[PDB]
Structure formats: structure tokens, C-alpha cells
Image (tube, coloured by chain):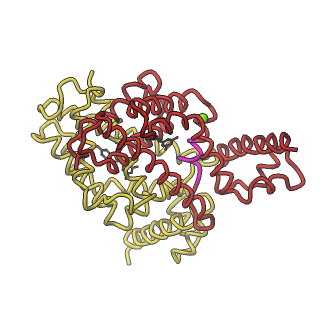
Chain colours: A yellow, B red
Amino acid sequence: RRTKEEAQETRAQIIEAAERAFYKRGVARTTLADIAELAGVTRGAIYWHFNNKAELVQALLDSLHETHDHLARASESEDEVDPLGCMRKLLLQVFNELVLDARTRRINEILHHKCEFTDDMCEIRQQRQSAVLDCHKGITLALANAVRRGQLPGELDAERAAVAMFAYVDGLIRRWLLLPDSVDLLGDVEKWVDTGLDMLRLSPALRK
Amino acid sequence: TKEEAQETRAQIIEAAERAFYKRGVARTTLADIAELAGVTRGAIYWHFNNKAELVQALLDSLHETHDHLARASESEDEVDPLGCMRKLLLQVFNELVLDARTRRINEILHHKCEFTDDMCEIRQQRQSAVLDCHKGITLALANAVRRGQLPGELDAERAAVAMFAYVDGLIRRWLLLPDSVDLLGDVEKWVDTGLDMLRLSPALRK
Ligand SMILES: Oc1ccc(/C=C/c2cc(O)cc(O)c2)cc1
Ligand SMILES: Oc1ccc(/C=C/c2cc(O)cc(O)c2)cc1
Ligand SMILES: [Mg+2]
Ligand SMILES: [Mg+2]
């Protein structure tokens, strides 16, 4: 109809086909030409939207923020009266979306288990570094806010606590992707979130 | 001869580490590895049925250093099982940071090895290996519980999952962003942060 609307539809068809192809065959051996054929678009069209497969990987990775942005910004705001509470809701939502949404599950499985870091495509590792560094910044801000509001210990090492928490969450996600039946991540989602928050609130090793 | 076969196998393993680390698992073939190792006339296929088996050899190689401390933590006659586990985890992080071989293998497993349907054995062998680690961790913690070193109502299974998640995530964080974690200089605090989760979180109780 209109150029932009047609372009948005094409882009979304490609991204969806990229998910399916990376998920079955992996990033290393999938080409844009392969994804174009699975999306039912021309090679000219796919290369118009994405210059290389690293950009297509980044589009998938960037798409994981959208759902959580509301709660993340709230937990990071200094004006929030209950920053720790926003973090808990954020973490529940992170796990809930991972188990229930096929798309989110698929993308995380791509990023964890179907995407390699090779100097052949150095930007895949550089983008991952940027993404994690950025999430670390946000976590540190929300923990520092929680400390200032009396919700976490006064001498918490916010930086180290932020690493601890991300490690725990990232490991649990990867474990659930590898062995879903090993973890009732949905039925016990509150215990899994609270286990991680307990570490930050109670461990003396995380204090200055 | 035994010696020359064992030496050829080792040369292949070290070559596989170099090739996988540079180009990744997905696109590296056994023939490429043999070319890098300088092994000829089909030698690699006598030592490894396929590429998955060679990946499993690298992962299996990580257990050797820690087997003593791991088995001790699992022994029902061990009087200090949690101390053996703390010694274990300190060694895991020290080796990661100090040993080029261990770091490089972990970077391969975490960041340079796809799981594909074409080669389903990689994912299945990783499942079995994590399940075996989890079985051992659970026995260590149950031992620690039995010996009054962790809370009597600890859910040993969920605790074992939590400890593994934290450790696995921290390694992977250190591999991606080394300068964000003083893993060696602060090793004791990183190990105790995780142990504190098990010792202290009410959410891991039954
Ligand atoms: O405070 C926190 C807020 C968010 C998170 C999310 C971590 C995460 C790690 C992954 O490997 C995949 C993913 O989709 C998310 C962790 C801590
Ligand atoms: O109690 C525990 C004993 C051992 C471990 C090992 C974890 C681990 C995770 C990795 O991704 C790589 C690795 O080389 C080791 C975790 C907990
Ligand atoms: Mg989302
Ligand atoms: Mg070793």
C-alpha cells in the first residue's frame, strides 16, 4: 500500500524467517539468501533491509528489551518509592515471557546455543558486550536506588551485586533452555526470583 | 604402539582447541583439524568417530583437575563436604583465570559451539554432562546437610540448580567481559556469594 507499511511488513517477515532458520540450522551456516527464500522475499529485498547477518542477529537481540522497558525504567528511576519491588516484577516478567512466549524462547536459544563468536564476524561478540554492559548499568542503578530506600543493606557493593544477579539469572535461563524438565521455572517462578534476590539482600560477601 | 597413539590423540585435541577457538565448531571439520595437527592417512578418524566426540573430549577434559575435590565432597565418609565444595569452586575459578587451556575450552563451549539438528549429539552430550554435574552437586549438598553445614530443610535439588546457574553465569560473564569481574583477585568473595545463597536464602528451603 504505502512504502513504509510494506517495508515494515517485509522487515517482520524476514525477522520471523531468520528466527526459524537460525533456530534450526544455526547462525554460522545460514546465509541471508537462505533466509530470503524461507521468508518468500527477494535477495534484493533482504539486503535492502540488512547489510549482513550480524545486523539480523542484532535485530533479534534488540527485540528482547521492548517488553521489559516499562519496569526497567521504573526500577532505575530515583523517584520510584519501591525500586526493589519493580526489579522483582521485572524478573518475574523476564521468566514468565521466556517460558510462555515461543518467540522469546527461540531467540534466547539462538543467542545462547546457536550463535558463535568468531573473528570472522567480530560484531556478534561486540554487540553482546555492549548489551550486557548496558544491562549491568541498569541493574546497578536499580540496586543503588533500593539501597537508598532502605530495601537492601546500606553497604551493598552495588556493582558486584549487579554481576551476581545477572550471573544467576543468565545461568538459570541457560539451564532451563538446556534442560526444561529440570526446572519448573513457571510454577516455581517466585522461588527462583527470590532465591536470587535473597543472595543480594543477605550475603555478607556482597557487602563493602 | 600405545605411546605414539596417546601422543597423536593429544596432538589432535590441542589442534582442535586451536581450530575451534579460531573458526568455531559449526564450520570446522575433522579434516581441517588433522591438517592443523599434521596427522595424516586418516589418523584422526581412528581416534574420533565424528566432530561431536571431539567436542565431548574437550569438555570431559575439564573434570580431571577437579575430580579429587569433587569425589571428596560426594563421599558420605567425608566430614567436611561443604569445605571440599568451597575448595572445588575456588579451584574452578583459579584454573579458569590462570590456565589458557581451560579458558579457551570454556570459551569454545560457551561461545563458539552451536547446537544443531544436523549434529544433535552435541546438545544431547551437553545435557547428559550437566545432568551428571547436577547429580554430583546434589549429593555434595545433601552430604553437607547431613553434616550440619547447610540447613536441614534445604531443597538439595533446587539449591544444586541455583549454585550451578550462578557459577555458570559468572564464568560466562568473565569470558565475555573480563575487566568487569576481578575473578581471581576477589575469588573468595565470588565463591562465598554463591555459597551464601544456599546457606541463607529461605527460598531454597522446603
Ligand atoms: O536485574 C536483572 C534484569 C534482567 C536480567 C536478564 C538477564 C538475561 C540473561 C540472558 O542470558 C538472556 C536474557 O533474555 C536475559 C538479569 C538481571
Ligand atoms: O557446585 C558446583 C560445582 C561445579 C560447578 C561447575 C560449573 C561450571 C559451569 C560452566 O559453564 C563451565 C565450567 O567449567 C564449570 C558448579 C557448581
Ligand atoms: Mg518481548
Ligand atoms: Mg583441568
Q: Quadrant of the C terminus of chain A?
A: top left
Task: Give percent across and percent down for residue A171.
Answer: 40, 47
Which residue is most to the left? A81
Residue at the spot x=49%, y=56% of the render? Answer: A57
Left or right: residue B103 compared with residue A204: right
Left or right: residue A81 compared with residue A191: left
- Up the image or down, B203 lies above or below A38; here it is above
Task: Give percent across and percent down for residue A111.
Answer: 47, 54
Whether residue B13 is visible: yes
- Up the image or down, A188 lies above or below A85; here it is below
Segment tinted magenta in the rendering: B106-113
**For this rendering, which residue is in front, B58 or A124?**
B58
Whether residue A31 is visible: no
- Up the image or down, B138 lies above or below A48; here it is above
**Across the whole image, how many numbered discs are drawn on residues?**
0
Residue B67 sits in quarter: top right
Residue at the spot x=46%, y=45% of the render? Answer: A128
Left or right: residue B19 compared with residue B75: right
Task: Give percent across and percent down for residue A80.
Answer: 12, 41
Residue at the spot x=50%, y=63% of the render? Answer: A49
Left or right: residue B8 compared with residue A56: right
**For this rendering, which residue is in front, A203 or A152?**
A203
